[PDB]
Length: 208
Ligand SMILES: Cc1ccc(Sc2cc(C(=O)N3Cc4ccccc4C3)ccc2O)cc1C
Image (cartoon, rainbow, N blue to C red; front, side):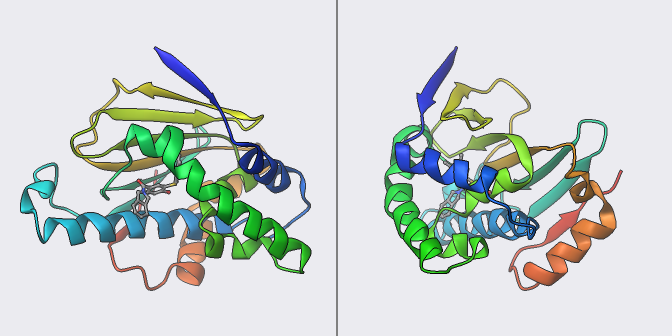
């Protein structure tokens, strides 16, 4: 059973701006998603210090980048704390509202789209390169969920019956047809070294 939700108006406006504005420096999406993975990994590691059983769902803390040219997907997998249903359908949108308004106002003051992560809404930079984003996520003591959106003001959430993840988040970027450079080994490596050089978890770039 699939539930369909409306983005809050401010977040829909942000996604439209990301999709419609001319902006050539699209590669920043990868830094923003890796940063989110790193923050999620930080949090499970921190919480496991007072409750070690939180690592029963998996002790390894890492980030994997997986291109698939046949499916035209770039997938980013981490074993961080994951997201609850409440995060997905209600609570993260509430935090995104204030960040979006601030980011909007910064853009009119002369800020650049690459600063999106300073306003806590860097995830939506995925829409610089993806026509559809599918997010599989598993938080301890909650179900595995699949979040999905092709923008247009709505997203879906369902309980996911695919391959169990144990714990963490998997962001599946269905790339636009003119954005397949982000499937190339040399290009991904270039971007990670330039923008994500000091991330404190092993990042593995899969090849095909
Ligand atoms: C709603 C939403 C928000 C971010 C993303 S992208 C995204 C989210 C996560 C995740 O599970 N997090 C992020 C974070 C930072 C701090 C603390 C805890 C947690 C949990 C990890 C990697 C990502 O690339 C996707 C969606 C669907």
